[PDB]
Amino acid sequence: QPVNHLVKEIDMLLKEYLLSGDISEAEHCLKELEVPHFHHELVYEAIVMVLESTGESAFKMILDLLKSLWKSSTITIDQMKRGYERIYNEIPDINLDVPHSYSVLERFVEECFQAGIISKQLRDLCPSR
Image (cartoon, rainbow, N blue to C red; front, side, top):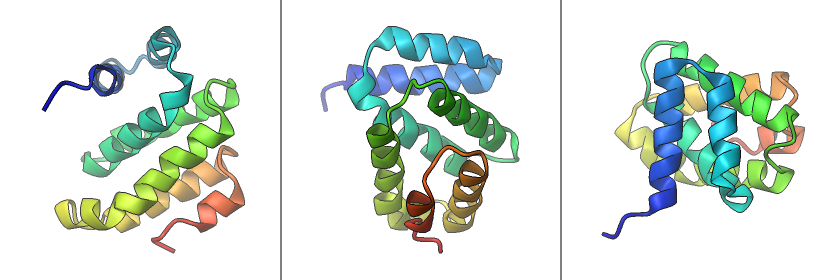
């Protein structure tokens, strides 16, 4: 299948962030991509990475990154909502591939909510609940 160059760039951005821990580099590189109508894919891939990870490091790092992106007005509310809603749609299959993803997703959603970055509606829509 032909390469989706922007999915690749988003995945590379997120992996560079997990490996370096550099939140500013991640934010700068996302802005340089100039893809504000595809930020839902950044959210989607980020959350998939949390679900596919081990230990607590990727969870916290991706939490802090989405916190900063929201709070800095880098991601619009429509793009935030679409990214989470995409995860909510695909979680049955992600959970088959990675058991207990419903529980991880739920903890992630609860922490996002506690951080002030998603509506109570969007929280409530999480299918783990």
